[PDB]
Image (cartoon, grey):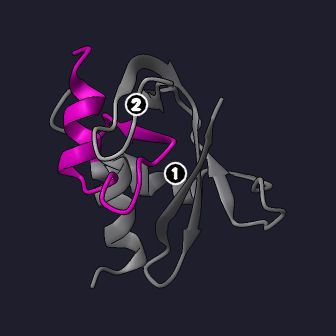
């Protein structure tokens, strides 16, 4: 039934790609529209190793006040998925926006790996 690290990979990792229909396909294929249309989500187009490496990079405060968040030293290729107004469950519609920004992830466990995508700056 998935571990926290595995869930992060399913919800936020897409190393395969470096379209306008991307989010519609991805949000559905990654099961992010089963219980409802997940409002917003971010996919990272970098290797798993490079993202896991962020856990040893810049320590920053998490949006929730916890101290286990880390910001990438280099910018990363990411895709932001935001639900449109016309989007009505179960036909979830999203706007695909590409960008190159630094990512902030929360890390936990042994091995210390990403378990939550906190923000992109």
In the displayed structure image, the side of residue 32 where residue 38 appears, left or right: right
Label for residue 43? none
Gap in Å between the C-alphas at discs 1 and 2? 34 Å
Tell me the crowding category of disc 2: few under 14, some 14 to 19, or many 20 or more residues within 10 angstroms, Cα based.
few
Query: Which residue is at the front of the view, 111 or 89?
Result: 89
Residue 77: x percent and y percent? Answer: 39, 26
Residue 28: x percent and y percent? Answer: 23, 46
Q: Which residue is denoted by mark 1 in the rendering?
A: 54
Q: Which residue is denoted by mark 2 in the rendering?
A: 87
Residue in the picture at 53% in, 30% down: 74
Q: From this view, report whether residue 20 is shown above or below residue 31.
A: above
Q: Which residues are magenta?
A: 19-47
* Quadrant where the image shows the N terminus: bottom left
Query: Which residue is at the front of the view, 95 or 102?
Result: 95
Whether residue 14 is visible, yes or no, is no
Residue 88: x percent and y percent? Answer: 39, 37
Residue in the picture at 29% in, 52% down: 48
Residue in the picture at 46% in, 31% down: 83
Residue 33: x percent and y percent? Answer: 32, 52
Q: From this view, report whether residue 21 is shown above or below residue 33.
A: above
């Amino acid at each position: 039934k998935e571990t926290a690290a595995a869930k992060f990979e399913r919800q936020h990792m897409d190393s395969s790609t470096s379209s306008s229909n991307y989010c519609n396909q991805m949000m559905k294929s990654r099961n992010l529209t089963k219980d409802r249309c997940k409002p917003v989500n971010t996919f990272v187009h970098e290797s798993l190793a490079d993202v896991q490496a962020v856990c040893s990079q810049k320590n920053v405060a998490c949006k929730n006040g916890q101290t286990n968040c880390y910001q990438s030293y280099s910018t990363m290729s990411i895709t932001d998925c935001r639900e449109t107004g016309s989007s009505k469950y179960p036909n979830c519609a999203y706007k695909t926006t590409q960008a190159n920004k630094h990512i902030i992830v929360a890390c936990e466990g042994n091995p210390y790996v990403p378990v939550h995508f906190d923000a992109s700056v």
